[PDB]
Amino acid sequence: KMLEQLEKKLGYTFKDKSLLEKALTHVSYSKKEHYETLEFLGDALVNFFIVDLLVQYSPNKREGFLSPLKAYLISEEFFNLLAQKLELHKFIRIKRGKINETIIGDVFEALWAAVYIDSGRDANFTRELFYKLFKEDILSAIKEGRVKKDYKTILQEITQKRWKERPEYRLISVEGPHHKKKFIVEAKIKEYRTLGEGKSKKEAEQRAAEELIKLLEESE
Amino acid sequence: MKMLEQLEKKLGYTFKDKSLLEKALTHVSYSKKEHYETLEFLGDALVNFFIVDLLVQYSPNKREGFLSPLKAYLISEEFFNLLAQKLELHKFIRIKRGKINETIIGDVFEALWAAVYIDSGRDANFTRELFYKLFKEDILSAIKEGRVKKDYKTILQEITQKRWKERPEYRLISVEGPHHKKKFIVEAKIKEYRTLGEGKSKKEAEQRAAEELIKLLEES
RNA sequence: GGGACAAGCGCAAGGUCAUUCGCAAGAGUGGCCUUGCGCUUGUCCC
């Protein structure tokens, strides 16, 4: 729509309108100049800000603790919540009935990739321009405790809030030598059942769980 | 300290807070109290940016499927070592239990620039140039040459040929789901080894089935 | 608020396999299994 209404929101005046154009143009809308390449650069760029910000204002600093957060801070979901705060879905150039939330994220990254370039690849600046919009929206997610729960955890919360029951894991075989063996567990709930190979029991379960989740993503 | 004063000369930056450079070289065993863990987490997302940004600039093509393989190498444990060795990091390390490994060299490398970044005062644009000053050419060369990181189907391709002089066979078994969200299921086979792979496409499905077959062969 | 079950993570312990050492008496590293405690969360009960 208006490649200037978005500039107002962002708080940046594009001195290369052409960029912002591409960063918003999807593939099927223009297989001549889409956002793909910019998404690539934007993904690494946005990833940096998020991580640099998360390493400062964070309770614990151990890897095992920061990974769960960053998993959400850069997840498609959290990337949509920040995009909505820009009404980005109203500036995208794409064919109708083909756009989903994934595409929004790509455009989000592709966006800051464009501001980075435009501003003469000024990191420090773009970084500040990034916080001046989402820093608090990010710190909040942190302060709250938002994270990307692991599979077994997820599958549990699902099964319980739909049947108030839990999944049942059963080892079915163990192959190879002790110092290095492969486990094969079976995840089952109700009438569903999947398998999962893993160096260890738990690792094999996380697998069988991930597969079960997918299976549950259909209907009741 | 006299050692943590040599690396500075090689790096081209004077640490206004040597306390950082220290932790950016101290392993976990060496000192549980203060290690490079958290710093490698930040340096990872920072070193990635410099590389990607540089890659999208000096590159023949720009499409995604052409940049992925490259980036796969430029942030590879292998390529990282080649850069660290040009600063003899394996000398300034700080361990304890057992000897060293290439992996650690990579972590400490990213953990290194993570320090510089904070040391200079979170100055990105600065650290960026300070990074290209002694690597830009080293990287652009890898690109110009065409150093990539072969995919799974290819890797499986080379293996199966250098052991049986034969190639694997991929067969589609099913395409479940609705026409607007169909998922393919191919079957990779070679001799008496088979695996399955789920994918949004036929090729994607194959890359999966392959990666699983490589691990089967990876056995013995 | 107090619990029952469960999950993830953390700390530790025991066992086992592999591996390294060795004044052969022992001593380390890693993979896996089991247990306890802590932290967080989910479903349930009070």
Image (cartoon, coloured by chain):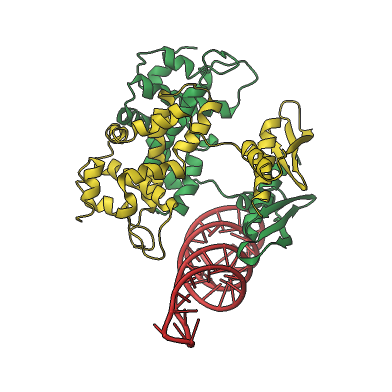
Chain colours: A green, B yellow, C red
Quadrant location of residue A127?
top left
Left or right of B64 in this view: A66 = left
Question: Looking at the figure, which quarter contains the N terminus of chain B?
Answer: bottom left
Left or right of A76 in this view: B44 = left
Q: Nearer the viewer, residue A46 or B23?
A: B23
Q: Nearer the viewer, residue B155 or B166?
A: B166
Q: Residue at x 39, y 18 (%)?
A: A7
Q: Is residue A38 above or below residue B162?
A: above
Q: Is residue A175 above or below residue A220?
A: below
* Image position, residue A47 (x, y; %): 44, 36
* Image position, residue C35 (x, y; %): 59, 73
Q: Nearer the viewer, residue C44 or A105?
A: A105
* Image position, residue A54 (x, y; %): 39, 44
* Image position, residue A16 (x, y; %): 38, 13
Q: Is residue B191 above or below residue A173?
A: above
Residue A36 in view of the camera:
yes
In this rendering, the count of numbered labels is: 0
Residue B53 in view of the camera:
no
Q: Residue at x 20, y 44 (%)?
A: B14
Quadrant location of residue B79?
top left
Question: Looking at the figure, which quarter contains the C terminus of chain B?
Answer: bottom right
